[PDB]
Length: 49
Length: 49
Image 1 (tube, rainbow over the protein chains, first blue to last red):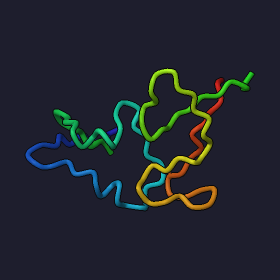
Image 2 (cartoon, rainbow over the protein chains, first blue to last red):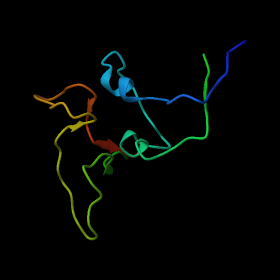
Image 3 (cartoon, rainbow over the protein chains, first blue to last red):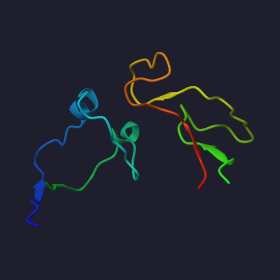
């Protein structure tokens, strides 16, 4: 009920490690794709745990 | 009636008036998908609900 929300900025939101990492098994992007994520920018990302 | 299928993954968008009947397993990453499965390997065909 107290899930955090960390606004991310002034730092590159690298995602290659996610692709490189083999620990993750399920990874679905229903709005974008990793292929076009290279040339696609997001205003800000909130890390909610 | 689930006899109706559709393709969900492709290397590239097919040209107009092209029929695709390929059934090879789709690999999300660059690593080869040997055998019938592999890392993030899924069947590209899904039935209609």
